[PDB]
Image (cartoon, rainbow, N blue to C red):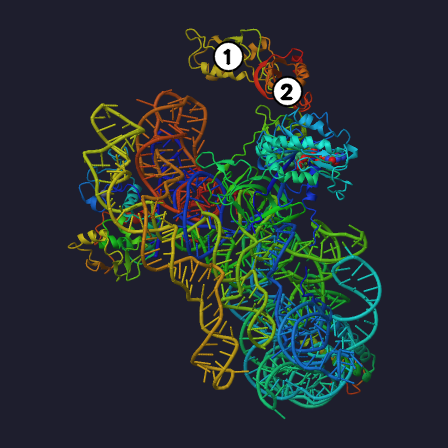
RNA sequence: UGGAGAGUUUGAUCCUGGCUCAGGGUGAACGCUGGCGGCGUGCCUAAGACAUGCAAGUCGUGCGGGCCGCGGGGUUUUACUCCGUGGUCAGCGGCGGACGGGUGAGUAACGCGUGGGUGACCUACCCGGAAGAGGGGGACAACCCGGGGAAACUCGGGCUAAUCCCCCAUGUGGACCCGCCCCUUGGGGUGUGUCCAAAGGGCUUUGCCCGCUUCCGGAUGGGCCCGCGUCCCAUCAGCUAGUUGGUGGGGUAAUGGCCCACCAAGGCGACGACGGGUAGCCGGUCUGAGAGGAUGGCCGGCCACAGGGGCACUGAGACACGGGCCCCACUCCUACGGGAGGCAGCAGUUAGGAAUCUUCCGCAAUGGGCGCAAGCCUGACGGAGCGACGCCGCUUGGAGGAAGAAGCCCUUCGGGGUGUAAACUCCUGAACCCGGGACGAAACCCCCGACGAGGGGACUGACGGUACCGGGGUAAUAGCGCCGGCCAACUCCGUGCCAGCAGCCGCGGUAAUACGGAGGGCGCGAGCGUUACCCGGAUUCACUGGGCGUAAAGGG
């Protein structure tokens, strides 16, 4: 009637549920950042962006994101942010983005 | 660990005329033989049950109802039988049949009076018949306490013990001694029993006259050694519905019912050609007969079989000589009254079902896969009695019907299909009304075919009364293939059953030698479509006494026409007469019913011919028209309540009563 | 299997005498010696001219009947000799000749091929040691065909091994009546085999 | 090293030309016969449905317990019942269930084949190299108690372990944006800034073994892209809006209208678009002198699909055949409130059909997953079974033996034939008997060594008491087709355009080598015929290798 491979499903669910979060996290967070950065919040933007970044390479560790999955998202985050901070702002605090 | 002494085998059949108690009696046997309860549907043909160190195989199905055939089939396979009787039905005219068809094969049986509780339930009354009707030597084996509504306990003479029944749920029984009165009644019947048993054991004979009582063990031996010979028939009793006399009838089983050994060996034939017994030794060649196929949803095709010699084995290989085929028996199976017992083998004399086999239909003989490729007997000959016209509506259904029998004729070879060799329409051979009737449901339902069901047609014939002579001319002279043929003939009627006779009555040769062949093929021909309705104008002599010709125009053919004209008209002219088919029939009937039997036949356009007695019966011969002869079964069986049977043959053709002349102009 | 049934009949038909029996065929009665004509009811009648086909068929039946060997096998061998590099005609004979049941007869251990076969079958023979029983076995160049030991003293073997003292054995074979041995020097040759058979025809027969 | 033609239009001829036959081949069926063995092979149809059993697991050397059998009992006695090891039951977590096995429905297409491109990528396990393994917290089952339920299970409290999760640290080093350097599609560097590592088990315990973390390289397997090749129908001629291109996003391991927004009107087609029919593709297979024609079963490679259809989750990998979700169809249980399923896995059932097998034995070998191992799983596989389905080998006898029995057939009645055939005579001795009896199996493990080389030792056979070997050993299965010509093989009797034959031409209408029987003969032989289908013959679609005045064919 049954085969103890559901042990694989039970897990299947757990894991999903886990990364499912750091997943949607980086999302909302990725936004909160570019938002300000564009809004003008020069430094306090770079702050969040620096956080977002972490949470990314952080998720890269497990099986959530991986390879360039992280690196890609980054090259776009600290890409658009910097391309909104030039909307007259001069990268204030020493956020991620390099001089 | 033998578990099979053979001498412990009881293969029995419950026969008896409808109403009775056959079926109900069986489910009951299948409750006692297996209520067990120890500190731990006739679901397929034959079933096994255990009763006091004895395996019993039952095949309840008889029914009698017109078509027996089946009853008489299980009968051949099995060894014993209970002829249940309806105690109530006293002025019982059909108690009969059943049995007179049992010794018909050669098998032993005991009697049971079932409804000993239903009004009119008079035990004696049966025996007052079981020797008055069939006339055997039954032996009172019990005497009921409380005739009918007052059905309490019962008494077994042979063992002078009394039992009782406090209910009808089959629980509160017990062996309580004789109740005050009664007693006396016993003795005498227990003496006659022993007096009867005397005609078997001399030991139980002297001891009788000396004043000693036969041992309860040597006494049984007599009765048993007496039944098995078809000399006596132990009668018992009890309301099978109220569970009474059953557990006692079950003893009655083993105690008097033959074992696969007490019975006479089956004959079979070698591939060379010579009879030979088949010995019940579970170590000789493997010889088994088949008798019932059934489609199981779980295991598929099932082929219930009765082994005689050798022993079939689970996961082996068999061989059916009948249809020269190598079947591979994979699994053996025994039907228990409630589950599927999967056993590993059936030793000679045992019965069950095999799984596998594809070409094995009814009556098949299966031997080892090297054994003498022999074929048993089985030859049963139950032909038909009632048929019908079946015209499959538009040619569409004419097919659904072909398949109809293409599977229905394997699932029941107790019939015959035939295409009337004279008029498309097909006949459906049956063995009694009901028979064809219920086919008409399945063949029309589970086959969705929707055709017609009226009656056959009659192979009429044309001919004449007065002799005539007319001209046969043809000539067509316009310019070339002249076409010139002409002849004169002498047409003259011949006795009803004369045939076809022509006469080469040409003098010098006014009609060339080479053209006569053709002038005949022309006359012979034309006679096809009658002058009245279009039927084989027969029973006449033709005389070609004249006709001329032309040197160039004549033709082999031109003459075939001219002669086909001379005839095409002599019959029209000599006053035609619509002849019809007359049959020879022989109704076997007790001169009891005879009186009306003959009547009815007279009022059937028929004229009687005689009645030279036979057995206790009497035979009647006579002629009749096939038209006024349809569905005769259910008319003969009417004027005889069942005790009537007939045959039928063709004879001659004869004029229709004129009133039936213009009738047929259809 | 190896035919069986009237033979000094085929001896006939082909009308070119054969030694299917061996000894007797030599006596005044190889059959054809007395009735040199096709069997059957007609047989002795003016024979219509043969068709271009009949001819080749008969030359095949001739050659194949000599070695008495199922058309099947006969054909396989031919179909081999063809694809074989060398004048197919000779070649074919080459193999036919290399059959153990034959080498035996040739070496004289048996009076007839029909007999030589039975011996081979019943292990009365041996090749370089291990005994063989397949008549069809094909001998290579430089083999020793000997009579087994259990055999050695069996009437038949003697008598036949007897008539051998004196007679010579094909240039492609060397026999030692004593040790009942015999080597397969070389592959027989076209002429060595004086057969009343033309290979050319037979070939042409397998070309249609 | 390879090429054969014939019959049939006429009174006769020559040409054209169609038809037809002899040859080979088959997952075959059907008919009549059928003795042995070896190696192959066996649902071609309903990709219809399917009872039953088994086809995927495994680690206690990752972790905490429940239950059971042992130690010593914790305390002074049972008490808060701990400990170490060996069974167990599930729960955790780790890998493996994406390989293996089945199938051809779909698909005319970068699906396949072949040859290449990845400055456009991925790769668990396995090798080699470099550097690490520093602190802390934290939940959820199991378990207990309580509640819903027919069932499948499920909900609520409360504990608790771990190689499970999470934060801080160090970052050999890797990831990102910016700038410069080499390079040249996103390839290597390099400086500022920023971001990220980790896990612990076993022993013989400062040393190993198995793991962990990051990074570079190898190896293996893959994704995507491109040139060329890849069937029939023009009585399918025009097709196209995410359509073709662009900019910017999203998405991905990665390119890309793969998706979206918004611009621009373009993209494709007689070199055959679009539409319709059919079909899984190849190595190969059959035939053929070759070119070519057919074809794609078994074995190997790729693809695709797992009742029909859609979809994501987990994960190195899947949109997963014995995983999940939803729709529909069908099967089953139901306390009818809701549950359980998917044999195109092995075997088998039913239906269909002309037709295609045992619910077999073994993990002994090979191979695969899990483990340090012992070992466990393994219908993959290694074998057995049934089937002349194919092919190969073998037997039913060998040597004698009559101017020649019998019977039967023909006859000119002299006789001819069957025919050395039988008989009979010797001789060998399939089958069958006692007896002996394998190869496949030498490693993993263990001991010396140094758990390396090398040396030594032990346990391992389903088939199988089979093959085979020695001894003993009886004359011991033949059919089927054909006999007018092509085409080898002819007489008699029946029959009378009847019955029947028949591939073609034709045979049969009182003497039939053509029907039916007999004798005899020819062919082949455990086979022999028939029916399907493909090549050949057919230079009869002609590239090799054809034609058009009148034969079919020149367009007004
Ligand atoms: C179950 C048993 O034992 O008999 C049953 C089963 C039964 C013998 C049936 C009578 C008759 O159909 C029988 C035939 C031959 C009817 C024709 C086919 O369909 C056969 C395949 C079928 C086999 C058994 C069957 C179906 C029975 C009856 C029927 C009684 C009918 C009436 C109207 C009284 C019986 O026994 O009375
Ligand atoms: N009252 C009563 N009825 C009975 C008894 N035995 C049988 N019957 C009835 O007989 C009728 C037919 O029974 P069945 O055995 O099927 O008849 P069969 O098949 O012809 O033997 C039913 O009404 C049964 O109830 C009995 O002992 N008592
Ligand atoms: Mg009944
Ligand atoms: Zn001769």
Residue at image x 59%, y 22%? B647
Q: Which mark is residue B279?
A: none
Judged left or right of residue B218, residue B323 is: left
Q: Position of residue B241 (x, y in %)?
A: 74, 38
Up/down of D12 relative to A33, above or below: above
> From this viewpoint, is residue B447 visible?
no
Up/down of B291 relative to A30, above or below: above
Q: Nearer the viewer, residue D258 or D234?
A: D258
Chain of the residue that carries numbered disc 2 in the rendered image:
B
- Counting every numbered tag in the picture gives 2
Q: Which quarter is ligand 2 in?
A: top right
Q: Position of residue D282 (x, y in %)?
A: 51, 59
Q: Position of residue C69 (x, y in %)?
A: 31, 48
Q: Quadrant of residue A66?
A: bottom right
Q: Is mark 2 within 8 Å of ligand 2?
A: no
Q: Secondary structure at mark 1?
A: loop
Name the outermost residue toward the front: B210
The local crowd at label 2, few if under 14, some if 14 to 19, many if 20 or more residues have their Cα within 10 Å, is many
Residue at image x 15%, y 55%? C166
Q: Secondary structure at mark 2?
A: strand
Residue carrying label 2: B589
Q: Nearer the viewer, residue D450 or D118?
A: D450
The C terminus of chain A: image quadrant: bottom right
Chain of the residue that carries numbered disc 1 in the rendered image:
B
Q: Quadrant of residue B573?
A: top right
- Asked if both marks, 1 and 2, belong to the same chain, the answer given is yes
Residue carrying label 1: B475
Up/down of D533 relative to B133, above or below: below
Q: CA distance from mark 1 to mark 2?
A: 65 Å
Choose mark 1 or mark 2, whichever is in front.
Answer: 2
């Amino acid at each position: 009637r049954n085969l103890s491979a559901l042990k694989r499903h039970r897990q299947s669910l757990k894991r999903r549920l886990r990364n499912k979060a750091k997943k949607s996290a980086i999302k909302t967070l990725s936004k909160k950042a570019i938002q300000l950065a564009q809004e003008g919040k020069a430094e306090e933007a770079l702050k969040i962006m620096r956080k977002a970044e972490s949470l990314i390479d952080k998720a890269a560790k497990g099986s959530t994101l991986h390879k360039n999955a992280a690196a890609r998202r980054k090259s776009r985050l600290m890409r658009k942010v910097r391309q909104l901070l030039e909307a007259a702002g001069a990268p204030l605090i020493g956020g991620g983005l390099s001089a | 660990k033998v578990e099979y002494d053979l001498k412990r085998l009881r293969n029995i059949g419950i026969a008896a005329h409808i109403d009775a108690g056959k079926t109900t009696t069986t489910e009951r046997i299948l409750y006692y033989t297996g209520r067990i309860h120890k500190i731990g549907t006739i679901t397929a043909a034959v079933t096994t049950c255990f009763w006091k160190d004895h395996r019993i195989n039952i095949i309840d199905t008889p029914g009698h109802v017109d078509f027996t055939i089946e009853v008489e089939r299980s009968m051949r396979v099995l060894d014993g039988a209970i002829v249940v009787f309806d105690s109530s039905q006293g002025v019982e005219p059909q108690s009969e049949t059943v049995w007179r068809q049992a010794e018909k094969y050669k098998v032993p049986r005991i009697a049971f009076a079932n409804k000993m509780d239903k009004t009119g339930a008079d035990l004696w009354l049966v025996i007052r018949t079981m020797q008055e009707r069939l006339g055997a030597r039954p032996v009172v084996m019990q005497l009921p306490i409380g005739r009918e509504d007052t059905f309490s306990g019962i008494i077994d003479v042979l063992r002078m013990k009394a039992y009782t029944y406090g209910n009808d749920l089959g629980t509160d029984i017990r062996e309580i001694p004789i109740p005050e009165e009664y007693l006396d009644q016993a003795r005498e019947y227990h003496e006659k029993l022993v007096e009867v048993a005397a005609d078997f054991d001399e030991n139980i004979m002297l001891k009788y006259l000396e004043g000693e009582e036969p041992t309860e063990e040597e006494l049984v031996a007599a009765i048993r050694k007496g039944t098995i010979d078809l000399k006596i028939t132990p009668v018992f009793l009890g309301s099978a519905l109220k569970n009474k006399g059953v557990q006692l009838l079950l003893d009655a089983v083993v105690d008097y019912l033959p074992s696969p050994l007490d019975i006479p060996p089956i004959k079979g034939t070698t591939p060379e050609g010579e009879v030979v017994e088949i010995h019940p030794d579970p170590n000789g060649p493997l010889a088994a007969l088949a008798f019932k196929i059934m489609a199981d949803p779980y295991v598929g095709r099932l082929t219930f079989i009765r082994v005689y010699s050798g022993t079939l084995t689970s996961g082996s290989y068999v061989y059916n000589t009948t249809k020269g085929r190598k079947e591979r028996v994979a699994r053996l199976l025994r039907m228990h009254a409630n589950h599927r017992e999967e056993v590993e083998e059936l030793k000679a004399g045992d019965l069950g079902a095999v799984v596998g086999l594809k070409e094995t239909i009814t009556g098949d003989t299966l031997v080892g896969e090297d054994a003498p490729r022999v074929i048993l007997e089985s030859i049963e000959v139950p032909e038909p009695v009632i048929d019908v016209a079946i015209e499959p509506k538009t040619k569409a259904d004419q097919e659904k019907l072909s398949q109809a029998l293409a599977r229905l004729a394997e699932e029941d070879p107790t019939f015959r299909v035939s295409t009337h060799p004279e008029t498309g329409q097909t006949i459906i051979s049956g063995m009694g009304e009901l028979h064809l009737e219920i086919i008409v449901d399945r063949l029309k339902r589970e086959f969705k075919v929707d055709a017609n069901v009226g009656k056959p047609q009659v192979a009429y014939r044309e001919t004449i009364t007065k002799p005539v002579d007319v001209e046969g001319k043809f000539i067509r002279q316009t310019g070339g293939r002249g076409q010139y043929g002409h002849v004169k003939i002498k047409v003259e009627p011949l006795p009803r059953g004369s045939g076809f006779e022509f006469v080469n009555a040409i003098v010098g040769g006014v009609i060339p030698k080479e053209y006569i062949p053709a002038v005949q093929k022309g006359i012979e021909e034309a006679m096809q479509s009658g002058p009245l309705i279009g039927f084989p104008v027969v029973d006449i002599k033709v005389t070609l006494y004249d006709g001329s010709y032309h040197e160039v125009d004549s033709s082999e053919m031109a003459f075939k026409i001219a002669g086909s004209m001379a005839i095409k008209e002599a019959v029209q002219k000599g006053d035609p007469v619509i002849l019809e088919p007359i049959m020879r029939v022989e109704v076997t009937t007790p001169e009891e019913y005879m009186g009306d039997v003959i009547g009815d036949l007279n009022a059937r356009r028929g004229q009687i011919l005689g009645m030279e007695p036979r057995g206790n019966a009497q035979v009647i011969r006579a002629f009749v028209p096939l038209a006024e002869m349809f569905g005769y079964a259910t008319d003969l069986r009417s004027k005889t309540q069942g005790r009537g049977s007939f045959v039928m043959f063709f004879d001659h053709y004869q004029e229709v009563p004129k009133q039936v002349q213009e009738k047929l102009i259809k | 299997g190896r035919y069986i049934g009237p033979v000094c009949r085929l001896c006939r038909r082909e009308g070119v005498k054969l030694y299917l029996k061996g000894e007797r065929c030599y006596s005044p009665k190889c059959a054809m010696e007395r009735r040199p004509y096709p069997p059957g009811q007609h047989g002795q009648k003016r024979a219509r001219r043969p068709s271009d086909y009949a001819v080749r068929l008969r030359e095949k039946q001739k050659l194949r009947r000599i070695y008495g060997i199922s058309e099947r096998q006969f054909r396989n061998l031919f179909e081999e000799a063809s694809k074989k590099k060398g004048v197919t005609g000779s070649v074919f004979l080459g193999l036919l000749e290399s059959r153990l049941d034959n080498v035996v007869y040739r070496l004289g251990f048996a009076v007839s091929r029909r007999q030589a076969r039975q011996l081979v079958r019943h292990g009365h023979i041996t090749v370089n040691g291990r005994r063989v029983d397949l008549p069809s076995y094909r001998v290579r160049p430089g083999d020793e065909i000997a009579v087994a030991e259990k055999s050695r003293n069996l009437e038949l073997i003697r008598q036949n091994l007897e008539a051998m003292k004196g007679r010579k054995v094909g240039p492609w074979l060397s026999l030692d009546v004593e040790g009942m041995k015999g080597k397969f020097l070389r592959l027989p040759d076209r002429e060595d085999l004086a057969l009343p058979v033309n290979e050319q025809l037979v070939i042409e027969f397998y070309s249609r």
